[PDB]
Image 1 (cartoon, rainbow, N blue to C red):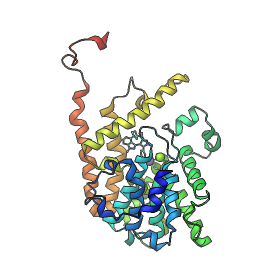
Image 2 (spheres, rainbow, N blue to C red):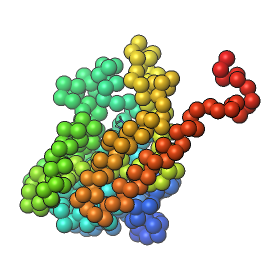
Image 3 (tube, protein in one colour):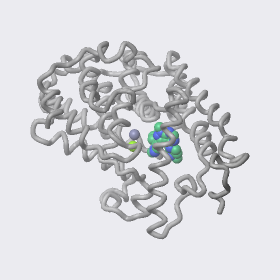
Length: 339
Ligand SMILES: CCc1ccc(-c2c(-c3nn(C)c4ncnc(N5CC[C@@H](N(C)C)C5)c34)cnn2C)cc1
Ligand SMILES: [Mg+2]
Ligand SMILES: [Zn+2]
């Protein structure tokens, strides 16, 4: 490809040159034209010193980036831009939060790689639709749970074992297999069921306080950080939140259409005739998003602004609620829609 040419010959742009605001929480990675994002991945890893630290071969890494990028389909939400903006938020965590005092470098490295790979080959439909619609993935995976996530992992593994893409094949067998373990745990942790299982443990962790010598704290923190990244679109301003809803509901309603055409009734939120958006968004923000970011703040006080921004985005939903009632006449002055 021609993308492959340019990445392999031009050089790794330093990070400041992408945007003077690039390492800030107020930065919106979705502003970056899709065509610059593989480059940026490279700059982020460079700026974290990983390329030098773990002695990664540059061409192999370039090839791996591109494979990961094209292993994403194009549903409205779960596409390469989602994956890039989740990896970018992992980068901010390392730059802003000083994870190094809580995590080994190999763990931080794995989180970042996992971020890029965590939704590989997503089709825009969720775990219950896979079962509900008895697909090959459910066939493969459904008896162990997390259908989509096991598929994401499996695709990551398939890219790694593609000639010239194995950015880890020079690690010791000990480090190589630690790296596969960590990616499997982290990708699996992106299922909301997983997160709901470990919630008390996370609360406990923040309650007793973080213990650097407790291996299980390392594991739990890794899971919290992955869910932080995966929800990071809710940490920017109202403009991002609104646009994120458009893309998320377009995907849910599409799946809902397909559930109706197969002869099931979709859940409310996936049904475009019943889904009432402000209320679903407010529920999501209150029950899932806010608690994840409150936990982040409990363990790294410099993460407080993330939480208040999420809270603040939930407030806007409430403020615009009323606009989903047609008062007066519709713009075209006709009750045509009513028929
Ligand atoms: C464990 C952390 C986690 C990870 C991914 C998701 C997620 C979303 C999502 N991501 N973001 C940024 C959203 N912003 C608003 N609403 C969203 N939906 C509305 C309904 C809600 N659902 C889970 C009941 C999610 C989402 C879409 N699919 N999945 C699986 C959710 C939680
Ligand atoms: Mg996912
Ligand atoms: Zn995701």
